[PDB]
Image: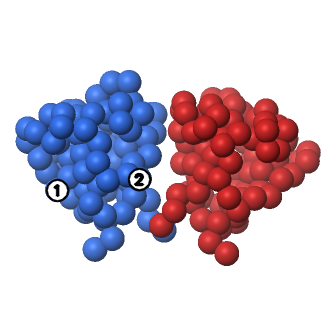
Chain colours: A red, B blue
């Protein structure tokens, strides 16, 4: 399909993994996770937000894989919501 | 084409305006201005960056109009480069 991403609880794609194809207003409520330590964008372009409901700091994810938060330009693994860039 | 945006030096679509369809690594050099106070996204989806060469804070622009910087989630008129999200 057009949108798909895998997010991991630990860096270097380790720990538990969750896969999704839709926007997520709160990763704590949906995935019971406080942070994202690494991920892989398999399809589409996405954006990470610091706070719930797409508020706070924004990070564009337009590459393929990210082993650590620094790879998507963040000084911390803090992420609470994310969504697809629809086009 | 797929990407087109108009940037304004003053809020609410007033003041000097430039229309462009390509990425801009530095507005001071390309457009002889230092702050964008409003803008219209006519075609495509873009992203504004705090510092030149796409560095610093990021702001997604996926709606059509923004009357003030706060509308793209910025606390100040600080934006010095921007580019198209090519999908």
Reading the image, the residue beneath label 1 is B19
Rounded to the nearest whole Å, what is the CA distance between mark 1 and mark 2?
Answer: 17 Å
Please give the name of the residue rendered at 77% of the width and 50% of the height, measured from the top-left corner.
A7
Q: Is residue A9 above or below residue B69?
A: below
Q: Is residue A36 visible?
A: no
**Location of residue A72 by image quarter:** top right
Please give the name of the residue rendered at 35% of the width and 30% of the height, measured from the top-left corner.
B70
Q: Residue B26: image x %, image y %?
A: 27, 43
Subunit under mark 1: B
B6 vs A24, left or right, is left
Q: Which of the two residues, A14 or B36, is positioned nearer the viewer here? A: B36
Subunit under mark 2: B
In the current view of this chain or complex, which residue is farthest to the right?
A: A15
Q: Residue B56: image x %, image y %?
A: 45, 34
Image mark for residue B62: 2
Q: Residue B18: image x %, image y %?
A: 14, 51
A4 vs A73, left or right, is right
**Other residues around mark 1 within 10 Å, as few (<14) / some (14–19) / many (≥20):** some
**Location of residue B27 by image quarter:** top left
Helix, strand or loop at label 1? It is strand
Q: Is residue A50 visible?
A: yes
């Amino acid at each position: 399909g057009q949108y798909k991403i895998q997010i991991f609880e630990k860096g270097d794609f380790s720990g538990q993994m969750y896969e999704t194809t839709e926007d997520c207003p709160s990763i704590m409520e949906q995935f019971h996770m406080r942070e994202i330590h690494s991920c892989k964008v398999l399809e589409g372009v996405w954006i990470f937000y610091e706070l719930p409901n797409y508020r706070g700091r924004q990070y564009l994810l337009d590459k393929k894989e990210y082993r650590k938060p620094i790879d998507w330009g963040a000084a911390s693994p803090a992420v609470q919501s994310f969504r697809r860039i629809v086009e």
